[PDB]
View 1: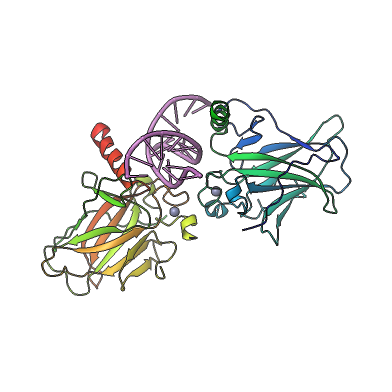
View 2: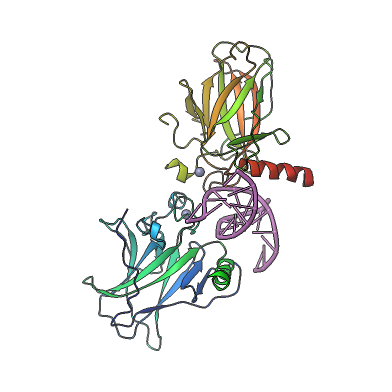
Length: 197
Length: 197
DNA sequence: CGGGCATGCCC
DNA sequence: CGGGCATGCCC
Ligand SMILES: [Zn+2]
Ligand SMILES: [Zn+2]
């Protein structure tokens, strides 16, 4: 078992928050976000855009880290890993990592030598002029249902904004359900919330 | 892809056939056999008794081999293997083999150097006096549904009676569905046969 | 594309 | 134990 990183929202002195794109209505849309549930529903190994918004400009050398943790108390201490099947199936990501970043030449994949937890880090880049946010494309390389991996257990993705010195500048999180039919599953979960939540 | 061993029934000069035990009615009975479907429904890593019946006594040194093949034409050439998850989960069986034999001190596990197919072999032993058959206890170490293994594809188990020289004395086969609820699944499949087969 | 099934497992 | 759900995928 491994010590558990904080998932406590900390928007901090830079006013850090996440944003997500609206999606179509398809049963099998590739990625769709539920504001009511703060939960992303997406397909495995498909683009998941996450926007970074800040009110104040982070210092040069700021980094953006993503890490998965199991949401439920009883699974929090277990490291989130790729299942053995998909592990055995891009040149930089270790096969065991669940979360990848696409289209970034400065991506780093880390394995914590104490907690054994995986994370993926890219440099923070400010928005282009006239733009309000910066977008990172994440991929999740297993379904939430994968036998021997997540095994139908919900996870959070924790996004931390960190300075080059390691100071925590901001932290936000969202739940993720990686699945074959993100539209179906989002709509059922939202209905279940309203009907019996 | 690998060449495909025969599944053609050959009861042969010794009158070789298989027998199976009757089971209870439970939804999750450990092992149950459908004569109408020539199909065993069983749970993973649980005892599956198979009886060997002969009309004439096989010669000394006769062996009994079990091997799995995919039943459907489109999958026949693929070697049946343990899924990566269960492979990574008795002292003699290689982790990759689907079929094991329990309670036999002369069991051999083989990996064919040409076809790459797995088989498990035990000596043939004649029934005790007053007994009509000899029983072997097999185990299947994945569910039929296992991602990265059988993946919901049906298999046959082929049992061959072979002399010590390698001559084929007899061959029989039965379909297998390894699953959580053998009673449920047998009853549904038998109903489907009657209703729309 | 959206309807619908099989199947491990609910806690 | 038997009812029933979530979820990958039907070919
Ligand atoms: Zn997986
Ligand atoms: Zn398996």
